[PDB]
C-alpha cells in the first residue's frame, strides 16, 4: 500500500491558515518561520518578481496593493456571474477578470509580465506555504494532507479546494468540514457520555453552524447550515464604508480612488475591530493618509455594533435552522463550541448566550486553531500509525440536490443533511441524448436553486428487441463532492462511465500545467531558503568569532600580536564584505566561509 508519510491537517482560511500534525499522542500546531501559529492567507509578487506568501505578503500590502492577493476563498469555485463575486470584487484592490466564465486574479509578476491566476492557484500558493511550514518542523517532505472547507461550501467550491491541494503538490486524502474538525478538537479528549454539541463557526469570510452527537469517539453531524459570504472581512468593510463617508464629509475628499490610502485604512480598521473585543473605544490613526493630511478618528464598540447590527443578528438564523432540522430544542444542547476568530466579538458571544438562555460556551478552545487541530487528528487517523484513539465521523451534505431532465421530470434527489457517502439512481428510457441539470438548495422548484452542473449522456446504441435502459447514479463521496456515472442496464455489460460536468471544472491536463507553474516557484523558494540559510551560517560563524577573539582570557590570551592582526582583520574583512553582499549567490557565501576557515584554522590548531 501507499506510504502517505506524515499527513498534515490544514485549515485553509479566508484571512488565516493554520497547519497541525498528530504525533506521539498529541497535536502540534506548527509555528511558521516567523514564529506564528497562524499564517495570513496572502500572496504577493514584489516589483522584482519574487513570490511572497503569508506574513511577508501581508506586510507589504500598503506598498503594493494591486499585486497583493487575499480573500481568494471568497472567489474559489465560483462563477463570474455569482452575485457574491460581483459584490466582493468591488472592494478588492487586485484586478479580477472573467476567464472561462470564472473570476481570475490578474497581477503583475515581474519582468513586465501580467499573469492571470485561477483562485485555486492562489489558494495553492497558500497551501504550499503551509506545507513548507510543516516540512521545516518535521525535517521531511509532506505529500498528503487533510484540508478544511466550510460545511456550507457547495460542490464546485469543494472540488476547487481539493484542486488547490493538488496544485500545491498535496494528495488531499480528505476534505473535512470546518465545524466537524472543530468538534473533534472539543471532543477528542472527552471521557464523558453522549453529548449534543452545537458548533458556531464565524471566521474571516464564512459562517457555519453544525449540530453533532458525540459518543466515545463517534461524531455525527445531525444538521448543518451557514453562509459562505459572511465573516470578519464583511465587518471590516462595513467600518471602511463608514469612515470613507466620514472622511468625505469632514474634508470633501473621496479617498476611494487611492488604493494605498484605502489599504492603510483597512489595516487600521482591522486592528481597531480586534481592540474593540476587549475595549469600548479604539483610535484609528494614519500619518499622511491622503494628499499629506492625517487621519485620526475614534471608533466605539457601540458604533461598531450598530454598523454591523444586521450581520450579527443574521447569524442566529442558521442556529434556528439546525435546531429545527435536528428536531431538537435549546435545552437538548450540552455544549456550545465557538470557533473562528470572529467569535471573539462580544456582541456575537452575547447573541449566542442570550439565544441559549444564559448558557456559557465551552472553555479552553482556541478559536483560531481549533479547526486545524481537528484536521490534524483526522490526518493522524488516516496516516495509520498514530496514537489517536478510535475516531468515527459521519458527516452530511449541506444542500438538497435535485435534477432537471430536459424532456423529463424535475425532481428532488438527495435532501440536505443526508449522511454521506450516499447515492441515488435514475433510469432514463428515452434514448437519443439526455441532458441532466443538477441544482443545489432548498427552494421548492428545483431549478430555482444554484446550478451545480449540466451532464449529457450522448452515446446510447440501439437495442433490437430490448428497452433503452440507461441508469444514472448520483453519488456524494466522503469529501461531500458529487460524481455522476452512467451504466447501460439493458445489455448486461457493467461499464460505469463517469459523465463529466459541462460547467468547466479544471481537467487533469489543466491541473498538471498549474502544478508545473507552482513547481517553478517552489524551485525558487528552495534556492532562496538554501541561499539565506548559508548567508546566515557565514554571518553566525563570523559574529561568534567576534565573541571568541573578544575572549581575552581563553582564545584571545593565546594569540600573538602577528596572529590576532591576521584574525581580527579576517573577521572584520568578512563582516565588511557581508554587509555589501547580502544579495550574493549561494556559491560566494560558501567561498567566504571557507576563506575565513583556511585563515582561522592554521592559527587555532597551533
Ligand atoms: N479579537 C478579535 N475580535 C474580532 N475579530 C477577530 C479577533 N481576532 C480575530 N478576528 C477575526 O477573525 C478572522 C480570522 O479568523 P481565524 O482565521 O479563525 O483566525 C478575521 O476576520 C479576524 O479579524
Ligand atoms: Mg480566516
Image: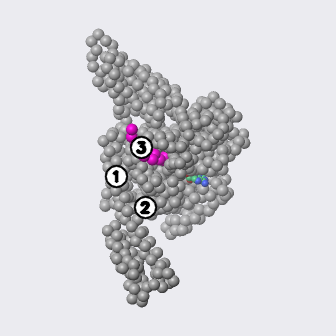
Main structural element of the magenta stretch: helix, strand or loop?
A: loop
Q: Rounded to the nearest whole Å, what is the CA distance between mark 1 and mark 3?
A: 20 Å
Residue at screen point 37% across, 77% down: 601
Q: Is residue 184 visible?
A: yes
Q: Quadrant of residue 44?
A: bottom left
Q: Which range of residues does the magenta coloring cover?
A: 1-10
Quadrant for the C terminus in the image: bottom left
Q: Quadrant of residue 570?
A: bottom left
Q: Residues within 10 Å of mark 3 (few under 14, many from 20)?
A: some
Q: Which residue does the image show at 52% across and 29% down from the upper left?
A: 418
Q: Which residue is disc 1 drawn over?
A: 519
Snapshot colouring: one colour
> Is residue 556 or residue 372 the one in the foreground?
556
Residue at image location 37% in from the left, 49% down from the top? 117
Residue identifier under label 3:
4
Label 1's element? helix
The residue located at (30%, 25%) in the rendering is: 458
Number of numbered tags placed on the structure image: 3
Please check the rendered image and state whether residue 3 is part of the magenta-colored stretch, yes or no. yes
Sequence-first disc among 3 and 2:
3
Task: Give the residue number, with chain letter if any, for mark 2.
Answer: 64
Give the crowd class for mark 1: few <14, some 14-19, many >=20 residues within 10 Å: some
N-term mark: 1 or 3: 3
- The image shows residue 414 at horizontal and vertical percentages of 49, 26
Amino acid at each position: 500500500s501507499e506510504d502517505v508519510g506524515t499527513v498534515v491537517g490544514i485549515d485553509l482560511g479566508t484571512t488565516y491558515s493554520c497547519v497541525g500534525v498528530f504525533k506521539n499522542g498529541r497535536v502540534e500546531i506548527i509555528a511558521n518561520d516567523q514564529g506564528n501559529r497562524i499564517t495570513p492567507s496572502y500572496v504577493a509578487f514584489t516589483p522584482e518578481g519574487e513570490r511572497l506568501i503569508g506574513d511577508a505578503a501581508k506586510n507589504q500590502l500598503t506598498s503594493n496593493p494591486e499585486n497583493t492577493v487575499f480573500d481568494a476563498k471568497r472567489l474559489i469555485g465560483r462563477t463570474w456571474n455569482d452575485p457574491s463575486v460581483q459584490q466582493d470584487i468591488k472592494f478588492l484592490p487586485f484586478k479580477v477578470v472573467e476567464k472561462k466564465t470564472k473570476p481570475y486574479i490578474q497581477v503583475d509578476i515581474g519582468g513586465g509580465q501580467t499573469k492571470t491566476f485561477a483562485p485555486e492557484e492562489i489558494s495553492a500558493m497558500v497551501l504550499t506555504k503551509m506545507k513548507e511550514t510543516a516540512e521545516a518542523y518535521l525535517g521531511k517532505k509532506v505529500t498528503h494532507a487533510v484540508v478544511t472547507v466550510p460545511a456550507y461550501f457547495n460542490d464546485a467550491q469543494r472540488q476547487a479546494t481539493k484542486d488547490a491541494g493538488t496544485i500545491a503538490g498535496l494528495n488531499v486524502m480528505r476534505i473535512i468540514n470546518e465545524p466537524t474538525a472543530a468538534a473533534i478538537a472539543y471532543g477528542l479528549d472527552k471521557r464523558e457520555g453522549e453529548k449534543n454539541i452545537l458548533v458556531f463557526d464565524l471566521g474571516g469570510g464564512t459562517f457555519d453552524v453544525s449540530l453533532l452527537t458525540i459518543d466515545n469517539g463517534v461524531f455525527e453531524v445531525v444538521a448543518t447550515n451557514g453562509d459562505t459570504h459572511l465573516g470578519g472581512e464583511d465587518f471590516d468593510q462595513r467600518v471602511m464604508e463608514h469612515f470613507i463617508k466620514l472622511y468625505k464629509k469632514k474634508t470633501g475628499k473621496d479617498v476611494r480612488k487611492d488604493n494605498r490610502a484605502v489599504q492603510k485604512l483597512r489595516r487600521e480598521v482591522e486592528k481597531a475591530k480586534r481592540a474593540l473585543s476587549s475595549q469600548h473605544q479604539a483610535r484609528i490613526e494614519i500619518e499622511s493618509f491622503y494628499e499629506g493630511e492625517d487621519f485620526s478618528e475614534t471608533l466605539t464598540r457601540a458604533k461598531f455594533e450598530e454598523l454591523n447590527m444586521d450581520l450579527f443578528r443574521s447569524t442566529m438564523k442558521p442556529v434556528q435552522k439546525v435546531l429545527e432540522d435536528s428536531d431538537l430544542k435549546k435545552s437538548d444542547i450540552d455544549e456550545i463550541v465557538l470557533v473562528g476568530g470572529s467569535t471573539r466579538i462580544p456582541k456575537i458571544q452575547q447573541l449566542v448566550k442570550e439565544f441559549f438562555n444564559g448558557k456559557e460556551p465551552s472553555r479552553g478552545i482556541n478559536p483560531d486553531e481549533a479547526v486545524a487541530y481537528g484536521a490534524a487528528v483526522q490526518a493522524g487517523v488516516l496516516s495509520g500509525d498514530q496514537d489517536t484513539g478510535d475516531l468515527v465521523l459521519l458527516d452530511v451534505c449541506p444542500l438538497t440536490l435535485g435534477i432537471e431532465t430536459v424532456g423529463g421530470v424535475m425532481t428532488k434527489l438527495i435532501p440536505r443533511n443526508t449522511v454521506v457517502p450516499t447515492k441515488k439512481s435514475q433510469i432514463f428510457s428515452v434514448g437519443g441524448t439526455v441532458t441532466i441539470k443538477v441544482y443545489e438548495g432548498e427552494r421548492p422548484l428545483t431549478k430555482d436553486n444554484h446550478l451545480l452542473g449540466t451532464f449529457d449522456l450522448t452515446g446510447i446504441p440501439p437495442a433490437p428487441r430490448g428497452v433503452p435502459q440507461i441508469e444514472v447514479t448520483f453519488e456524494i463521496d466522503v469529501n461531500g463532492i458529487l460524481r455522476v456515472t452512467a451504466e447501460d442496464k439493458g445489455t448486461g455489460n457493467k461499464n460505469k462511465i463517469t459523465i463529466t460536468n459541462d460547467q468547466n471544472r479544471l481537467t487533469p491536463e489543466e491541473i498538471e500545467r498549474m502544478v508545473n507553474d507552482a513547481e517553478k516557484f517552489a524551485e525558487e523558494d528552495k534556492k532562496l531558503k538554501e541561499r539565506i540559510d548559508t548567508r546566515n551560517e557565514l554571518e553566525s560563524y563570523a559574529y561568534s568569532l567576534k565573541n571568541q577573539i573578544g575572549d581575552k582570557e581563553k582564545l584571545g590570551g593565546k594569540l600573538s600580536s602577528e596572529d590576532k592582526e591576521t584574525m581580527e582583520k579576517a573577521v572584520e574583512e568578512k563582516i565588511e564584505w557581508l554587509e555589501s553582499h547580502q544579495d550574493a549567490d549561494i556559491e560566494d557565501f560558501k567561498a567566504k566561509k571557507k576563506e575565513l576557515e583556511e585563515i582561522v584554522q592554521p592559527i587555532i590548531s597551533k
